[PDB]
Image 1 (cartoon, rainbow, N blue to C red):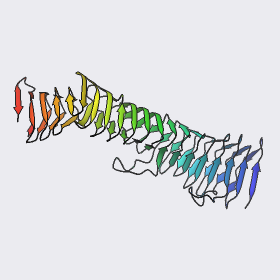
Image 2 (cartoon, one colour):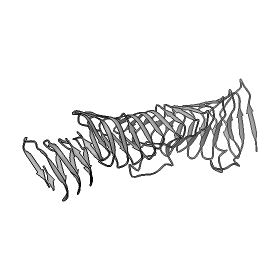
Image 3 (cartoon, rainbow, N blue to C red):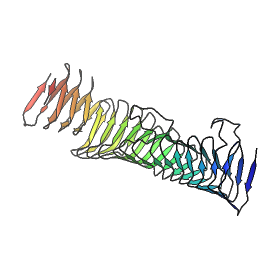
Image 4 (spheres, one colour):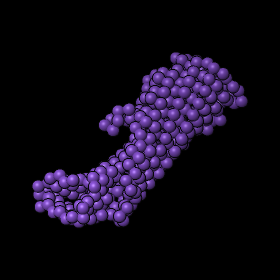
Amino acid sequence: AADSVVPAGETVNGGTLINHDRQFVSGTADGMTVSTGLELGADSDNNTGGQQIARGGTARNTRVTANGLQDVMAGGSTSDTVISTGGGQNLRGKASGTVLNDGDQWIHAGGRASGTVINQDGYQTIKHGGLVTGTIVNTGAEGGPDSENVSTGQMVGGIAESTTINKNGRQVIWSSGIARDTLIYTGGDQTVHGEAHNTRLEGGNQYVHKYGLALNTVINEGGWQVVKAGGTAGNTTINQNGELRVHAGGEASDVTQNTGGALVTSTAATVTGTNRLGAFSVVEGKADNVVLENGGRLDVLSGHTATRTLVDDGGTLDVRNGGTATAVSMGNGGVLLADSGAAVSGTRSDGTAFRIGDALM
């Protein structure tokens, strides 16, 4: 019902916005508490009230609470907005230091959010043409790898740059989205339907879904890059105690498999790269020179072949009915599983020969 304007060059300190009141900020508004403008929710066209930052205006230390809407127009700016309990920031200008404590931030085309902190139950949605940098993601993956929650955390339909994903943090990259230069700690995860470039798994997980593309993922201790059917990973580095898992119909090309790195796949996947014994490939049902250790595993399916597989400590070679593995080299701690109809031959730890055609060593 009531309406106020902060002209350019003027500054207003404090205040509360309730019952659909509106503050039109062309100057500076510091410490406003915004508790109206979003009563009907984000999917309604009939909301009224809230704080509007026009071109050249600025807001500082704003609190957005339940039903509160801070609307930042192109050319407007905010610093250190704290969003709690079902408030939201609609961003078409610039925001710095926004904290989401179960609040929403929507970044529209041309909007830019730097340093947003997504705390528990917070929700950052980046639309096509929107950009965020330096985001800290602390929520959305509380439920672990089995949780398909996408209602909290960071949803990327535009571009996210320099994101840190901490324990419990979840980033989802939709088909049109791009994440560049992401750091993912243990307990954090990133799901790729769009594109990811330069991702560091410092214990965290990256799931590459159908049509997703992950470029230059570095997998350090505890990290996990999973490539589903129809997903693609290019130029992955598997470091010690990291794992690359490529499902049937998934693709990983130009893999750098360093010593102690685990590769987990089957002969129905497509994998190429180099390991500590040179070039290796799993292509069109034929594996050559795969190195399995420290959790690595290769399933050789019916009609498929593997040659020159090194099964070293913590590696597992699993040859199904109708699969063939020749020149298998068994190291100490390596395991071979051969089902009934499997044909397997090689040499073991001892330099001694063996031939099959259930568990070995």
